[PDB]
Image: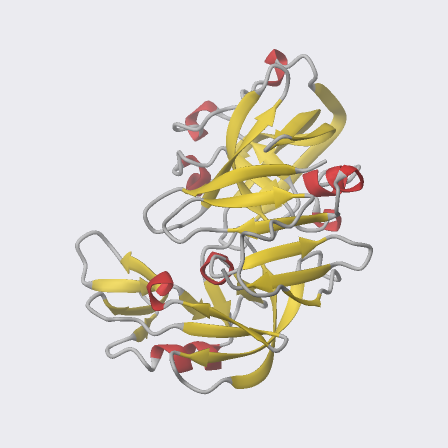
Amino acid sequence: STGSATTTPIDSLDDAYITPVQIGTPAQTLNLDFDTGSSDLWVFSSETTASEVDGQTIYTPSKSTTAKLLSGATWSISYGDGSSSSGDVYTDTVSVGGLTVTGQAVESAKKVSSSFTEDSTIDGLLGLAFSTLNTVSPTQQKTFFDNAKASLDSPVFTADLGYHAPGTYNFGFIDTTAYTGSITYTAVSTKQGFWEWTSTGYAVGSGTFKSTSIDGIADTGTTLLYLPATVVSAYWAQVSGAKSSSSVGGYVFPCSATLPSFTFGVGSARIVIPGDYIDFGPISTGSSSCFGGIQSSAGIGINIFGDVALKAAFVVFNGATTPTLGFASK
């Protein structure tokens, strides 16, 4: 089997991407944030504290003839950005772009933190990291990909995120028309539960490539590109007026700037992030100070190849017995 679904930016800055997901019988379609940095599929629901719902579409398990309460199971998750959610668990039928999993754990939120409430466009998350990170207790549950894998034509999914435009998540096949050149594959460590790999280096604009190993995670659920302070300083030094602002919470730059590109290495291959992908717009409405899309990972504890990087590539998440990651230009 295979699946193919369109993923759409939630706003004009590509702050995140939503993908429609069918849950239950009859189908209840929710727009979920597909997150290769976590491993819970959770949704706003009829059980979510009413004051914490503000415009989201909810899953109502009592209206699904295939929903079953997973007795005694609870979940609770906290994300890198400080947001969180928790609740109980159902199993139900879940379909993504024509690919159907029966008995998928659907984690129903009883509580969500303010940032989730405040974002009306995201109805929940669909985790695509390794199931070892799943938070369901006392019996850990599998991700949608893990459940689908054996049925797929090939044990892979691909992320093709657009810049200021829709893109695609495919399951079970590689669309050879969706990229240019070849896909370069690189080793993955699953030791931390992430799609963790090592970039071979970087360049800023038309500058020379610096060969240096940068361990980090391919994380579709993180908006920006978080890299070591040395790398980030080298980037922003090429932008007149750019500075790190502790009050704003990272590098800012004059909105009048033309940003340089940023290249990262995948083995001997190179992925070029155009400068415009690095512009996240005014820090506050009407400001001429703009927020940078490349930021320091210092104090995160890990480097993160988020959407800023991933959207410059066609990315293969290869879930073979030994997982790997593939990157192609597009």
Left/right of residue 64 with respect to residue 277 in the rendered view: right
In this picture the colour scheme is secondary structure
**Residue visible at 78% across and 54% down?**
320
85, above or below 181, in the image: above
> Residue 187's x, y, as percent?
72, 68
Quarter of image, res 64 = top right
318, above or below 238, in the image: above
**Residue visible at 64% across and 62% down?**
326
> Residue 200's x, y, as percent?
60, 78
Q: Is residue 59 visible?
A: no
How many marks the image carries: the answer is 0
> Residue 57's x, y, as percent?
46, 25
Left/right of residue 251 with respect to residue 8 in the rendered view: left
Q: Is residue 77 visible?
A: yes
260, above or below 278, in the image: below
Which sits in the foreground, 154 or 108?
154
Left/right of residue 293 with respect to residue 38 in the rendered view: left
Left/right of residue 31 with respect to residue 255 in the rendered view: right
Q: Which part of the image, by quadrant, shows the N terminus?
A: top right
Which sits in the foreground, 237 or 326?
326
**Residue visible at 59% across and 57% down?**
315
> Residue 298's x, y, as percent?
51, 72
**Residue visible at 58% across and 83% down?**
212
